[PDB]
Image: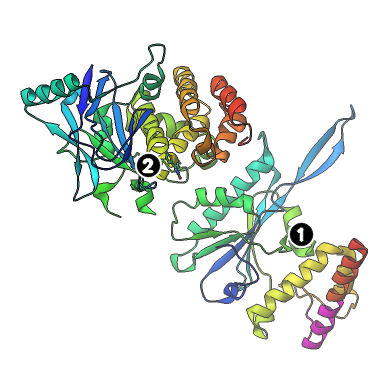
Amino acid sequence: MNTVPFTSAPIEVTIGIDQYSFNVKENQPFHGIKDIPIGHVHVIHFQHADNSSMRYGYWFDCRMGNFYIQYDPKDGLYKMMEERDGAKFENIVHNFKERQMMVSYPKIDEDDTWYNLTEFVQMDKIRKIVRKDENQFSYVDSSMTTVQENELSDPAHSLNYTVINFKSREAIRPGHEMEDFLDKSYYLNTVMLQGIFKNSSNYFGELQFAFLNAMFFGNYGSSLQWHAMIELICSSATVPKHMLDKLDEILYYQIKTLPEQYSDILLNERVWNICLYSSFQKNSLHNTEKIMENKYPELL
Amino acid sequence: GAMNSSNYAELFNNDIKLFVDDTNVYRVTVHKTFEGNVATKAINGCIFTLNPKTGHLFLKIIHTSVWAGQKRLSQLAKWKTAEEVSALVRSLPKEEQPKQIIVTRKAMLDPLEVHMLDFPNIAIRPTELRLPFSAAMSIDKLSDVVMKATEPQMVLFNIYDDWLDRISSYTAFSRLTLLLRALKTNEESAKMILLSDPTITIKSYHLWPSFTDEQWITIESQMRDLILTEYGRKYNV
Ligand SMILES: O=C(N/N=C/c1cccs1)C1CC1
């Protein structure tokens, strides 16, 4: 088990850790989060009591170093930082635990939710989408735009998702216009899987990270990226059978974890109706179709 | 953007543009089989690609053989149209390639766009206008060349005959759409009006009779007149 201590909590803020969250009061003696499960990525995220817009947060992996949080009164945000002095850090952690000023990562032992949402997400791939290589952890917020969004302004702050475009030369082989546009299999399997992602796990990984950014940060272009990567698979007549079954599990747990009140801002009607009911793979997402119908029949 | 009544005079500026209509590309007759089921037989069709400023018509004849052994023919029709439009633009010298292509039916957008990926600077646009180009096969000489064709074939026409020697593009296009509208809503009567007088002939290199200016005025009034009578009959107004 690992720990992310907090120096202080000077401003009222709702703190998220993965799918859990806690309200902390201005200058409440809060000093961090303990018992964080090793083995998966994690995200710690903040919504100030006074700015209900701007969500923001840090993706990290406790194996890659000792990380803590410190409010910066100049820039006005809780900042993640790395402590290189291992001894100094165990010392801070131990003292705060002794004083019991830390909340416990509240995992139910039956619950594989976070594993299921993060199965293919790897810290190394996150740091390629969020390029800032002086840090081991990755800052994402509500306002950050994607590279594809930027092509249609500041590139240092961009989400470098892999660009998917169904009406591009990349996606359409000359002489197979109609075929490739109606049946994206060659774009999925040769261009994206074999070409760019190298394997389905990296693709699922980006798909999942995009989802999480979409629902935890309210990041619009992440939601666009998640839907595009779903649509590419569902609009391909030829998908490896192992990908279809893994996809149905992946989407099931994403829909399951979805805030019911944001179902209409986070799920694109067209894409979902096409994947579940029109596409080549309409019959291959039974678990996903069953939870969508019982929980959001309106969207369909 | 979409083409509508507001931005209608843009048709007659000096930016090259083409209208593409696919309504006559895949044509069938429906008939009964010996066992009493229904079957279609295809007949030859055409892509109606028109420069509204110049009157140049690129009538690409679609021979039934194109359909042989193919499924989902109405969907394929849209892709074949786009493939042929694209081939037409590639065939044209650079200074003659259009800056816009305006499809008369929105279902052509994705196919043309995909086929025109090599021409990112050509804008594919829909239209909100209700253009009567489907009636192009009511023009006897165009129907005749389509139906006689034994192979794919491009045939070039000026759909304005020599009118531009005497009227603007704006006026020529209004006359053409008026005639085609009339031919659409009541072919028999429209054709009667055009040909009633045996002393007004069609030149061998023309599509329409050689009306004088005053006779065109009368003809247009007769066409107007027909279209509003028909609207009266059709809506019991
Ligand atoms: O337009 C959006 N609003 N999202 C709001 C959120 C606030 C907090 C979590 S999601 C994003 C697509 C989801």
Which residue sits at x=57%, y=39%? Answer: A269
Does the rendering let one see residue B161? no
Quick one: which residue is furthest to the bottom in this view? Answer: B214
> Which of A45/B97 is in front?
A45
Which numbered disc covers residue A97? Answer: none
Helix, strand or loop for disc 1: helix
Residue A165 in the image: state x and y as whole percent: 43, 43
Spot occupied by residue A136 in the image (x, y as percentages of width and height) = 18, 32
Task: Identify the image quadrant of the C terminus of chain A.
Answer: top right
Give the residue drawn at x 55%, y 61%: B101
Local crowd size for mark 2, using a 10 Å CA cut-off: few (<14), some (14–19), many (≥20): some
Q: Nearer the viewer, residue B195 or A16?
A: A16
* Residue lying at 81% horizontally and 78% vertically, measured from the top left: B220
Q: Main secondary structure of the magenta part?
A: helix
Q: Is residue B82 left or right of residue A205?
A: right
Q: Is residue B21 above or below residue A115?
A: below
* Position above or below: A108 against A266: above
Amino acid on which the number 1 mark rests in the picture? Met
Identify the residue position indicated by label 2 in the image: A163
Q: How many other residues sit within 10 Å of disc 1, few (<14), some (14-19) or many (≥20)?
A: many
**Residue B210 appears left or right of B82:** right
Looking at the rendered structure, the secondary structure element under dot 2 is loop
Q: Which residues are magenta?
A: B210-222
Residue B137 — which label?
A: 1
Same subunit, labels 1 and 2: the answer reads no
User: What is the quadrant of residue A270 in the picture?
Assistant: top right
The answer to the question of whether label 1 and label 2 lie on touching residues, with beta carbons closer than 8 A, is no
Subunit bearing disc 1: B
